[PDB]
Image (cartoon, rainbow, N blue to C red):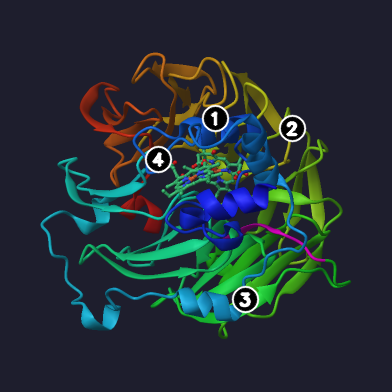
């Protein structure tokens, strides 16, 4: 009965077959982060300050539950998104060929910040020296993952949960092109020569290769092991020194490398893995791959050339290895990583792959960042009842040195530095949130920009260097 209800009240914005429109996509995969009870409240009483109105006046309890069950029930057949669908979605409001190649502003283009405002779905381009905005524009719904840049830092590529890819030109402050690569998307990667964008999708289970200059479609690459078993893509990353993309697969015992030195990467090199990999991190020299297993079997280290498993790292809880950092301690490489289920910062010695120590915190965090100029590692306890402070771990002592509390009570997380590391920018993820600027040397606040749930911020210089 929910189908008819959806057609009369919802399809006006959430689109036919729930694929999206004025409002977001409402497939089961789309709502994986939304509990049905929460989806039920949003339907009855709407979202404040959004175009989603409450329907409690037109629907009763039975109809309410019917819609909820309908949204979370799998369709009789899996929805498609073909090459034809992708090409038809392409738009090009400002092709590069028609735009000059000089910045239209004073700000240092290498110190600009891309700031995601996920509360009202906007993006701010921020002068990294004055800490003031030079542009702001609405974005696609639910941006996730770090926006990727071109090698020269001029272009930036956004990926939305619902599969929309946006190409923005920082020099002219204009949207260049957009295309829908899939229905449920993880992340995208840009090749180190600037030619290619590779989109890793959950739904469909495929990779989508786009031309990096206009987001046009090059080829759709189904994700399936050598036996033909279909799989979702966990994540895609670029290995510059290897001039290749590296793809983690969610559901098959396979790992892919797609080289692009000799042209469009459409043929994968398949490496067998003993256990599934959800996310991974590259060693500073891209020789080794640190992978986190879905099962609590600890971490896994793999040599990329051969594909051999060289070490197994026991890890407390479930480490978010994909966002870890490295640095030199006693002239030796060390690796730190936050955690999703336990309040700990796991630190690993790269030399013998031996875990050094486990730093205790007030709860599991989501992010970790540093800089060659900062003597600390900056992490958080994003996922805990205590979550309003940003922890600064001294690199040499491996102990929580200082703590920053931008807005007591509200959730704080994610750090990004200016290109010279002189300042650090922190986010307060709240409806009454803010982007807060701190002197990374004196650790004193300098400026505060109110924003509606600002998420990540990304410095051009640091990301392309
Ligand atoms: C694989 C991956 C990346 C690296 C992508 C890249 O940049 O190439 C990433 C990055 C990110 C980055 C990029 C930061 C960076 O510094 O690069 C941010 C801000 C972020 C905010 C969130 N992440 Fe993320 N995130 C996951 C996966 C990932 N997140 C999950 O699996 C998880 C736990 C659940 C999910 O449904 O995806 C998840 C939940 C969250 C959130 O709910 C956050 C807090 C808010 C949101 O928008 O959903 N993730
Ligand atoms: C256009 C005005 C809409 C109609 C008609 C319906 N919905 Fe909606 N919905 C719309 C928007 C723009 C948004 C996004 C709000 C925001 O966060 O900015 C939503 C949101 C939802 C959600 C939450 C999705 C999520 O958080 O992941 C749900 C579950 C939802 N809408 C369901 C829903 C149903 C069942 C509708 C018919 C009764 C319906 N919506 C109508 C826009 C519009």
Mark 2 vs mark 3, foreground winner is: 3
**Residue 82 got which mark?**
3
**Residue 405 got which mark?**
none
Quote the CA–CA distance across marks 2 and 1. Answer: 38 Å
**Residue 41 got which mark?**
1
First reached walking from the N terminus: tag 4 or tag 3 = 3
Mark 1 vs mark 4, foreground winner is: 1
Mark 1 vs mark 3, foreground winner is: 1
Quote the CA–CA distance across marks 1 and 3. Answer: 34 Å
> Residue 121, relative to residue 98: is it above or below?
above
First reached walking from the N terminus: tag 1 or tag 3 = 1
Pick the front one: 241 or 450:
450
First reached walking from the N terminus: tag 2 or tag 1 = 1
Sort mark 4 into few (<14), some (14-19) or many (20+) by Cα contacts within 10 Å: many
Q: How many marks?
A: 4
The image position of residue 100, as x and y in percent, is 18, 77
State left or right for residue 52 relative to residue 298: left
Pick the front one: 459 or 225:
225
**Residue 315 got which mark?**
2
The image position of residue 185, as x and y in percent, is 58, 58
> Residue 94, relative to residue 186: is it above or below?
below
Residue beneath disc 4: 371
Q: Secondary structure at mark 3?
A: loop
Image: magenta residue range: 230-237
């Amino acid at each position: 009965p929910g189908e008819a209800l959806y057609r009369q009240h919802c399809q006006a914005c959430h689109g036919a077959g729930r694929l999206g429109g004025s409002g977001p996509t409402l497939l089961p995969e789309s709502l994986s982060r939304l509990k049905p009870a929460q989806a039920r409240e949003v339907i009855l009483h709407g979202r404040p300050a959004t175009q989603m109105a409450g329907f409690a006046g037109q629907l009763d309890d039975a109809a309410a539950d019917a819609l909820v069950a309908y949204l979370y029930q799998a369709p009789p057949r899996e929805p498609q998104w073909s090459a034809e669908d992708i090409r038809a979605s392409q738009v090009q409001p400002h092709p590069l060929a028609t735009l000059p190649s000089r910045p239209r502003f004073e700000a240092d283009p290498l110190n600009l910040f891309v700031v995601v405002e996920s509360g009202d779905h906007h993006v701010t381009i921020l002068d990294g020296d004055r800490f003031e905005p030079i542009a702001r524009f609405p974005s696609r719904y639910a941006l996730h993952g770090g926006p990727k840049f071109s090698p020269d830092g001029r272009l930036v590529y956004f990926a939305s949960r619902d599969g929309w890819v946006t190409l923005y030109d920082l020099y002219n402050l204009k949207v260049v092109a957009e295309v829908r690569a899939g229905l449920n998307t993880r992340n995208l990667a840009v090749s180190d020569d600037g030619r290619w964008v590779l989109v890793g999708n959950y739904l469909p289970g495929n990779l989508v290769l786009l031309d990096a200059r206009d987001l046009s479609l090059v080829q759709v690459i189904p994700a399936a092991d050598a036996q033909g078993q279909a799989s979702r893509v966990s994540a895609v990353y670029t290995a510059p020194p290897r001039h290749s993309f590296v793809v983690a697969l969610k559901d098959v015992h396979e790992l892919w490398e797609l080289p692009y030195a000799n042209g469009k990467p459409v043929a994968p090199k398949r490496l067998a893995v003993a256990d599934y990999l959800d996310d991974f991190s590259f060693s500073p020299d891209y020789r080794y791959l640190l992978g986190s297993s879905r099962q609590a079997r600890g971490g896994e280290v793999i040599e990329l050339d051969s594909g051999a498993r060289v070490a197994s790292i026991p890890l407390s809880g479930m480490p978010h290895l994909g966002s870890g950092i490295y640095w030199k301690r006693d002239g030796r490489w060390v690796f730190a990583t936050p955690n999703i289920s336990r309040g700990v910062i796991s630190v690993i010695d790269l030399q013998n792959w031996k875990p050094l120590k486990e730093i205790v915190t007030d709860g599991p965090g989501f992010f970790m960042r540093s800089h060659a100029d900062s003597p600390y590692a900056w992490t958080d306890t994003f996922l805990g009842k205590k979550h309003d402070e940003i922890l600064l771990i001294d690199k040499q002592t491996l102990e929580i040195a200082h703590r920053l509390r931008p807005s007591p009570g509200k959730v704080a997380g994610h750090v990004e530095f200016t290109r010279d590391g002189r300042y650090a920018l922190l986010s307060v993820w709240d409806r009454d949130g803010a982007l807060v600027v701190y002197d990374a040397h004196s650790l004193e606040e300098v400026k505060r920009l109110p924003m509606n749930k600002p998420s990540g911020k990304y410095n051009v210089g640091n990301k392309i260097g």
